[PDB]
Image 1: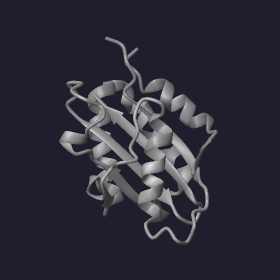
Image 2: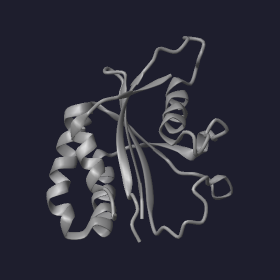
Image 3: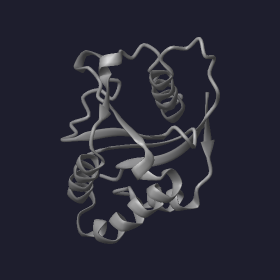
Image 4: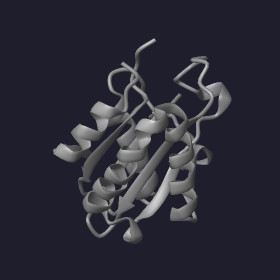
Length: 157
């Protein structure tokens, strides 16, 4: 399935994605994909679900997630804009220095111009995170099929 990869830059970014009413805003993680049988006709969906399961163990399971809870993102620019607006809102002036650090680290790990990008958007009746009063949330997957590698970026505030 998915194997967590070490990345010191991501560790540093994760340290800064905090407000420690102290709490963690989000987290960025890198995973290697393990080969699937060719008899699997929907390998991308399989990996997205496996990535959610690995990242959110033992809190939440996504094995019953529906295809329509996932989308392919047509535009890298749109995702960058969406993330930047959200994080600026949560981290404020401290995002100024974190912004380039974050995107540089992600690009070096996954090669953004080469990635297929996806999002997970839970159905309201199937939302594991519950009623946590957040104003926004995102769960993005940057999947480099050549590298067989996925960066998972999940935040809310």
